[PDB]
Image 1: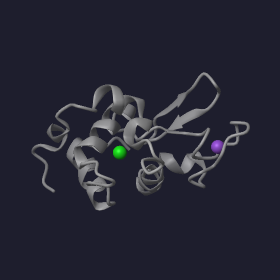
Image 2: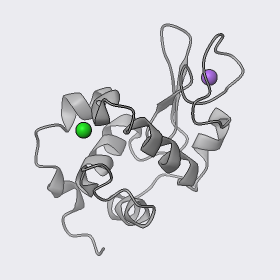
Image 3: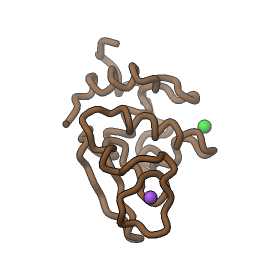
Image 4: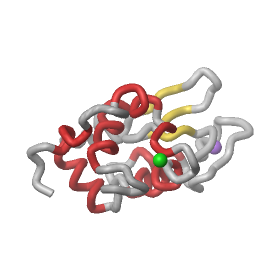
Length: 129
Ligand SMILES: [Cl-]
Ligand code: NA
């Protein structure tokens, strides 16, 4: 599923992400834009052989099992394929565990490089929430 901008904001708000650990809704939408282009089915392979999955590009070396990343952990306790569904529930819950582990949204390289310190509120302008 390829979300619209305001559609994804409303879905994110409903699942508890607005202001979660101090990050306003605009930050999560901006990170989803540059991680996956709003596409739940996006996958990308890293140099160490681990893979990134879904709307927020979650990594198989720490967070999910895909059966092909040796020695990795399954900290969110799911198969990585569940992160690709059109229902964003599993991606949201795992993301909540990630942003809580000490380093906040800095865990997402594209947030750090393209969203941090910008006007992230613009990402929800015009939306009915
Ligand atoms: Cl923080
Ligand atoms: Na894993």
